[PDB]
Amino acid sequence: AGVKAYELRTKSKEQLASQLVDLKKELAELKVQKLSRPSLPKIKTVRKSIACVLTVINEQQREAVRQLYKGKKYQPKDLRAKKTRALRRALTKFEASQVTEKQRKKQIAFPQRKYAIKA
Amino acid sequence: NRKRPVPKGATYGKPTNQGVNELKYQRSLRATAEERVGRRAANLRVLNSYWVNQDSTYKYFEVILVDPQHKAIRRDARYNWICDPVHKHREARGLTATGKKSRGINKGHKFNNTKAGRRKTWKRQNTLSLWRYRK
Amino acid sequence: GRVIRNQRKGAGSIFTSHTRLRQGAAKLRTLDYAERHGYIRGIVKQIVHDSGRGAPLAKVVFRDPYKYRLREEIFIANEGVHTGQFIYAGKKASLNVGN
Amino acid sequence: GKGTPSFGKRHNKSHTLCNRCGRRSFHVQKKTCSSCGYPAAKTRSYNWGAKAKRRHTTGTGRMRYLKHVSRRFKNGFQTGSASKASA
Amino acid sequence: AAQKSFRIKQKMAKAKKQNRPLPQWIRLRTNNTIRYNAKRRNWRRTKMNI
Amino acid sequence: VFQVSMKANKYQIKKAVKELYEVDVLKVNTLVRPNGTKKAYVRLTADYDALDIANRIGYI
Amino acid sequence: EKAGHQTSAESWGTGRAVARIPRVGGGGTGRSGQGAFGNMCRGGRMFAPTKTWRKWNVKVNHNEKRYATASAIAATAVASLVLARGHRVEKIPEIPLVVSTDLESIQKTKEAVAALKAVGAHSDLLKVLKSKKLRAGKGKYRNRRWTQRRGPLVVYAEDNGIVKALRNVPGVETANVASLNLLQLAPGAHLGRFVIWTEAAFTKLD
RNA sequence: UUGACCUCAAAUCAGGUAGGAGUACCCGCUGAACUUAAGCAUAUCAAUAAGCGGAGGAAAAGAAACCAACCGGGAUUGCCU
RNA sequence: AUAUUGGCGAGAGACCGAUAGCGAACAAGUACAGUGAUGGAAAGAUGAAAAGAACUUUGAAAAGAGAGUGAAAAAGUACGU
RNA sequence: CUCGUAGCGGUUCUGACGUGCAAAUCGAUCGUCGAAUUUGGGUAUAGGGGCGAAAGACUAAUCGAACCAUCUAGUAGCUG
RNA sequence: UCUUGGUGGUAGUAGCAAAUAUUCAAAUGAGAACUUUGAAGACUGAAGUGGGGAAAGGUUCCACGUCAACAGCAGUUGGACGUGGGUUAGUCGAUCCUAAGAGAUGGGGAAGCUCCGUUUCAAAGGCCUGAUUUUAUGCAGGCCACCAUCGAAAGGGAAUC
RNA sequence: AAACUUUCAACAACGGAUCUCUUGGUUCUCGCAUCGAUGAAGAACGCAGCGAAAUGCGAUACGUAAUGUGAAUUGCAGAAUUCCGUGAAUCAUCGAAUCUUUGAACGCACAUUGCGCCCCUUGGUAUUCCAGGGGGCAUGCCUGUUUGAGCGUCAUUU
Ligand SMILES: [Mg+2]
Ligand SMILES: [Mg+2]
Ligand SMILES: [Mg+2]
Ligand SMILES: [Mg+2]
Ligand SMILES: [Mg+2]
Ligand SMILES: [Mg+2]
Ligand SMILES: [Mg+2]
Ligand SMILES: [Mg+2]
Ligand SMILES: [Mg+2]
Ligand SMILES: [Mg+2]
Ligand SMILES: [Mg+2]
Ligand SMILES: [Mg+2]
Ligand SMILES: [Mg+2]
Ligand SMILES: [Mg+2]
Ligand SMILES: [Mg+2]
Ligand SMILES: [Mg+2]
Ligand SMILES: [Mg+2]
Ligand SMILES: [Mg+2]
Ligand SMILES: [Mg+2]
Ligand SMILES: [Mg+2]
Ligand SMILES: [Mg+2]
Ligand SMILES: [Mg+2]
Ligand SMILES: [Mg+2]
Ligand SMILES: [Mg+2]
Ligand SMILES: [Mg+2]
Ligand SMILES: [Mg+2]
Ligand SMILES: [Mg+2]
Ligand SMILES: [Mg+2]
Ligand SMILES: [Mg+2]
Ligand SMILES: [Mg+2]
Ligand SMILES: [Mg+2]
Ligand SMILES: [Mg+2]
Ligand SMILES: [Mg+2]
Ligand SMILES: [Mg+2]
Ligand SMILES: [Mg+2]
Ligand SMILES: [Mg+2]
Ligand SMILES: [Mg+2]
Ligand SMILES: [Mg+2]
Ligand SMILES: [Mg+2]
Ligand SMILES: [Mg+2]
Ligand SMILES: [Mg+2]
Ligand SMILES: [Mg+2]
Ligand SMILES: [Mg+2]
Ligand SMILES: [Mg+2]
Ligand SMILES: [Mg+2]
Ligand SMILES: [Mg+2]
Ligand SMILES: [Mg+2]
Ligand SMILES: [Mg+2]
Ligand SMILES: [Mg+2]
Ligand SMILES: [Mg+2]
Ligand SMILES: [Mg+2]
Ligand SMILES: [Mg+2]
Ligand SMILES: [Mg+2]
Ligand SMILES: [Mg+2]
Ligand SMILES: [Mg+2]
Ligand SMILES: [Mg+2]
Ligand SMILES: [Mg+2]
Ligand SMILES: [Mg+2]
Ligand SMILES: [Mg+2]
Ligand SMILES: [Mg+2]
Ligand SMILES: [Mg+2]
Ligand SMILES: [Mg+2]
Ligand SMILES: [Mg+2]
Ligand SMILES: [Mg+2]
Ligand SMILES: [Mg+2]
Ligand SMILES: [Mg+2]
Ligand SMILES: [Mg+2]
Ligand SMILES: [Mg+2]
Ligand SMILES: [Mg+2]
Ligand SMILES: [Mg+2]
Ligand SMILES: [Mg+2]
């Protein structure tokens, strides 16, 4: 059937690392039996179990780094957002809305009034 | 003058198109200056240029360039227009002052070919515009 | 209407000098303080043959004035110059063949 | 002897495989690819070669990364994860 | 050429593993139109051009 | 006789065979097969017996 | 625009014992040596390729448009042309068939077809939905799968539900008096559509 | 001795940024010939195709060194004329 | 406001209907040709469902002749007409 | 230098063949055979250009101007 | 002398005649001029029709099964078809070196694609310290003047019979 | 009189026309703006219990995570307590990852699976040799840091 990921989030780093080793033994041992048998579909289950454990280990490791660079400048570049190269060249929301104080005075003095041609 | 390369200086067109030596290069020497500086400094945007010297062989220009990634330009609202991507390499697209001069972009009856580009105008005035109910 | 052989020689493709076997550039010793105010003594060690040249080359060996090492200049050999001959280059030198 | 017995002496190679396009167009003496123009930075394309632009343009291969941009655009370039657990 | 590059042997290795007929169970699949391997190559009939 | 990664040299074959199968290797001869796979002839030292170890892996 | 031209063919000329049409160059594909570019050649361009700048929409004088609309409304009077154009209206009491303005505020399709049958448009209604036939050519797979007849046109002055209540009914078309489509009044350029007028519609026609 | 200044360097220094793609449309540069003129050199094709450089969702242009000569209009763009 | 034979998402048609329509309805820029730039195809349709012909017999076999299946085998994978 | 093999060429039969074995071969007869020889690999020269002990020869069966794509459905008082 | 596809007559015709040459028996098989074995006759005749290799090919090598198509007759055979097996290096090559040459950098030209140049008009740099307790061996002396890189499976080259 | 040749018909051939179909093309319209040094487009090689392609993916390899749906996939085979469930599935969606060798491609090179150098670390008695694991080392330019050069140059010094 295979390992379930929600179980593997609950284990620690040393529990998951040893589980990967035992899974790699089971893949190796089944790869031997596949040379005698004509069809061994259990390869697929152990192989996706390895991919599941290796995934959960990496999500534990990347979340440790996110707590390491938590709320400072200069995250690592793969922990930065991957919008679009143009979308991160991109004058930010603060910088695009910058207004010189000569323009800030005019915008406060004479904003667009709300009005209607009725009366 | 621009020397037309055309190896051994040879035509192979009409004799109207037979000149090699006397071709004059529609963009100015100030434009070549900014284009060559903008290639060396592609992290910057060329803003303007100005003559500083000349001799028998060279004209000398000083080119003003602006860093669109420095935060003293990305803030300070008087200058962060240069940080928008429409202004990537203005000097190659001819959007500098010497580019707009040599493109002919000026108001008036003297610039009827070149007001919104001579090529755009030529496309407009050579288009057969047909309507649904033919006029 | 085709480019002639005398024009094609300037492109220098198959018309270059066959210069593999040549012994070097046959030049004089570079003009320095030794050859401008006194002299310097050389020694012929070989009268060799230069490929493509009808004149023999004399390999004349001098001492470097400023560093302890030997500098081998390549001369065109003068008729009468032999191996083992001391050769004098400079201003104060004596008139002998090969000086 | 210009036809058939001259065809016997064809056992050399002018081009081998290009590293950039894998095409047997890398001229081994000129050190250049005849189709993609490697090692030059720009990729060899010509507007008189409209069929030749068609053979190698965007869409002809896998598009490992552009085949996902439209979905990421449509969702507004989300960051994070979906909320709930199950049905 | 008995002293190959690895890049030649790697493409030579790929061509041998492609040098098989169609698997017979593929012709039994639902809505299947594949009758045969249309990309079959022989050393005798078509040179594969490096 | 093993099938190994194409990226594995004769040191990484010898190191892996030693700590997976608790043997000692006398020699490794390696060839890349005409299907593009790498085949390792791993000969053990005389203290071990490759017939017993073949049953201990599971094949024959 | 590039149909029949995505081919680099040139003529072999004379001397080759075959006609001088451009033949495809190359070798080893079957296409090689085949004639190209002609209207008579397989794969070639057609003669005089059709353009989008052919005249599609045609201009009619506004008064000649209105001339035809007035003569079409006049033809939806006395019943000879209404019988002639189909339109089972023998058992109608009188033409023009004017019904009350209360039809304009019927909002249910059940109540709408009750009213049209009660004023005698039942046989015209059953003439449609017994004439549903499959189209007789390639147009049935150009989203034109089914053909049927035209039914009674219902003309109103105010929409207060009659358009939506008569929307699903096969063959029954609706119209404001302010518009009065000629494609509805004389379908097929055949004068005499069966028209049911509401009373507000009929007064407004002055 | 020492401390600046100016100019110029170096670093696997701290942070960044440029290249390539695509290119229908857009801004430039460069630039033909077939063709027509019942020949053809001006001309025309054509300030076009091909070639090169640079952008964006539009671009460019744009708030007058304008049009006018009227009782004057009023940035730019595009449609009808 | 304007352009948009590219991309993404739609909705249409008095368009074409497998020698047509894109070169390509199909593992198509594929198979293949060329040193290379480049060139460049052919090729859709059993049946409502494989029900794709068990079994017998003749033959070394392919297969035939029966038998069957099927509405139809004047639909037998060489398959609508 | 010579006779003459291997080799490298190609005189004559105007031989065979001439829908060939072959889009240049086959056979006999021949030139020359220690150098201005013959030859593999590497390398350089690219189209109005190269290269040419020079024949407008050769430059992938293409040469008094290669090949590929585009302009281009180039134009035709001419033939179907 | 249209285009694409299909089909005829010619016509069971022309032809399948270079490289001296085949023959007997048995075996296998449905079937043997052609397969296998034995016997015999012959030939290439060491500048070979013999043993290896270079380029090129790419699995054609080898085994088993098989004969619809292919081997211009045949076919039980096969370089065909189906399924597999097979290529082991410190010493053989590549890798390294330079050759003719190719080619970056500094720099100059060119509107530009890019061109020139390979030591130039550049501030172009690593090498050992004698030998170790304040040494991640330098925070030191001291030395060196050249200046990328690619280029040979026939040249140069560490070592296996 | 046959045979032969010719004509027509039937049945059988050859061939794939005709008719009918159509997950394709073509043209028009409407809406949107989103590639890449955070490594794109393109390429190569590989990956499935049995796949040569197309499609998908990258040694976590016709996929992992997550979320939604709610019991399949299937040509076989296998599994199907999991099936009133954190739950089938070649499902949909997709925000988390992985993403070989490349490629603008970036230590040097590339007709090579060729060769360096640095840091951390492991083993072989090892700072130096050999190997394994991890992480690096391109160019231009900008800002800043630090270390510097120049009798360019200013003060200041027994
Ligand atoms: Mg001139
Ligand atoms: Mg209109
Ligand atoms: Mg020739
Ligand atoms: Mg010939
Ligand atoms: Mg090629
Ligand atoms: Mg491009
Ligand atoms: Mg390789
Ligand atoms: Mg090997
Ligand atoms: Mg080996
Ligand atoms: Mg067509
Ligand atoms: Mg019809
Ligand atoms: Mg840094
Ligand atoms: Mg434009
Ligand atoms: Mg423009
Ligand atoms: Mg005209
Ligand atoms: Mg004319
Ligand atoms: Mg004239
Ligand atoms: Mg003329
Ligand atoms: Mg003009
Ligand atoms: Mg153009
Ligand atoms: Mg964009
Ligand atoms: Mg807009
Ligand atoms: Mg703008
Ligand atoms: Mg003003
Ligand atoms: Mg105005
Ligand atoms: Mg489009
Ligand atoms: Mg048909
Ligand atoms: Mg077609
Ligand atoms: Mg080829
Ligand atoms: Mg059919
Ligand atoms: Mg059914
Ligand atoms: Mg039967
Ligand atoms: Mg029937
Ligand atoms: Mg039957
Ligand atoms: Mg029938
Ligand atoms: Mg039938
Ligand atoms: Mg002689
Ligand atoms: Mg003689
Ligand atoms: Mg001889
Ligand atoms: Mg002759
Ligand atoms: Mg003759
Ligand atoms: Mg023949
Ligand atoms: Mg002699
Ligand atoms: Mg020889
Ligand atoms: Mg010339
Ligand atoms: Mg002559
Ligand atoms: Mg040509
Ligand atoms: Mg023509
Ligand atoms: Mg024909
Ligand atoms: Mg015939
Ligand atoms: Mg005969
Ligand atoms: Mg005979
Ligand atoms: Mg003999
Ligand atoms: Mg003999
Ligand atoms: Mg056998
Ligand atoms: Mg035969
Ligand atoms: Mg046979
Ligand atoms: Mg064999
Ligand atoms: Mg086989
Ligand atoms: Mg050796
Ligand atoms: Mg080197
Ligand atoms: Mg080397
Ligand atoms: Mg030597
Ligand atoms: Mg048939
Ligand atoms: Mg027909
Ligand atoms: Mg349309
Ligand atoms: Mg998997
Ligand atoms: Mg799930
Ligand atoms: Mg699933
Ligand atoms: Mg090499
Ligand atoms: Mg090296």
Image (spheres, coloured by chain):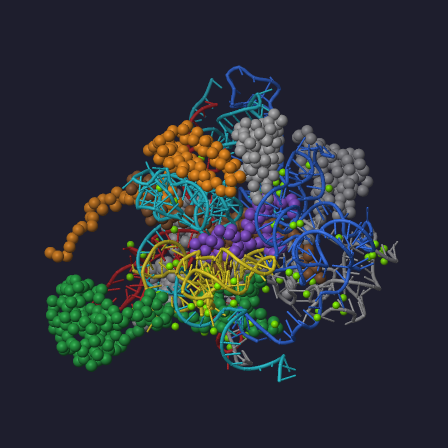
Chain colours: A orange, D brown, E purple, G green, H red, I yellow, K blue, L cyan
Residue B38 versus residue K83: which sits nearer the camera? K83
**Residue at screen point 33% across, 43% down:** D78
Residue B80 in sight from this viewpoint: no
Quadrant position of residue G178: bottom left
Residue B94 in sight from this viewpoint: yes
Q: Is residue K21 left or right of residue B87?
A: right
Residue K36 versus residue A105: which sits nearer the camera? K36
**Residue at screen point 16% across, 66% down:** G112
**Residue at screen point 17% across, 67% down:** G113
Residue K147 versus residue F41: which sits nearer the camera? F41
The location of residue L102, given as percent across then percent down, is 51, 44
Q: Is residue B101 above or below residue C61?
A: below
Q: Is residue G65 above or below residue L114?
A: below
Q: Is residue L50 left or right of residue K76?
A: left
The location of residue K132, given as percent across then percent down, is 56, 17
Q: Is residue B9 above or below residue K82?
A: below
| Quarter containing the C terminus of chain B | bottom left
Q: Is residue H53 left or right of residue K87?
A: left
**Residue at screen point 50% across, 71% down:** G41
Quadrant position of residue H4: top left
Q: Is residue B131 left or right of residue H4?
A: left
The location of residue F22, given as percent across then percent down, is 54, 27
Residue K149 versus residue K39: which sits nearer the camera? K39
The location of residue K61, given as percent across then percent down, is 66, 47
Tell how many labels.
0
